[PDB]
Length: 95
Length: 49
Length: 49
Image 1 (tube, rainbow over the protein chains, first blue to last red):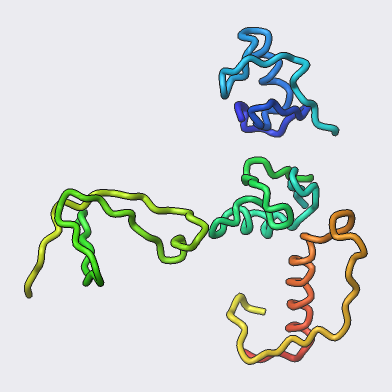
Image 2 (image 1 turned 45 degrees about the vertical axis):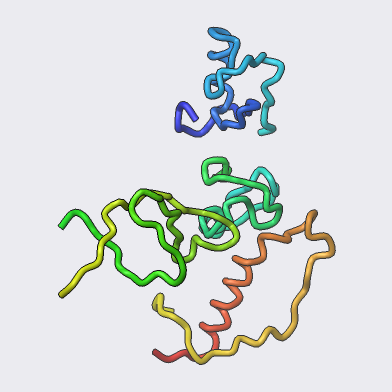
């Protein structure tokens, strides 16, 4: 979210952002709150991600183009398999 | 050149100036509401050639 | 072929092999595979512009 770069070490906050593990650690040390929401967050609450695109919800691989088209179609934002909401931003691109 | 105005014949209903209208989409007006962008048209008038 | 709309072509699916578990195996990632199958069917049918 903050860097707009690929995460060195992916993590997620309850906010549900993909700012690797850099942004969260700095915000917790300074504020003790999540930068997006401003809600209190602890380091423990952070969830670290375990280290062709994959959707987090389906956890399935898809052609990148196909995924993007489903996310942005008429109300087909969520996800073809799960139909759980999913954005382009939280699509993980595999190298 | 910058301002566009819509035209058409309503079927059954009458809101004169103040009442806004929830605009519908071409394909975004299904049961899954994607885009409405409700605005208010207070300059609705009839026209001639 | 040349990024043009297909017309007058019936792509008959002869035989298929489905996954036993769609949540475990590929269940939502078969549409690019079906697009590649349709492209290989249209390319190997002696096309004409």
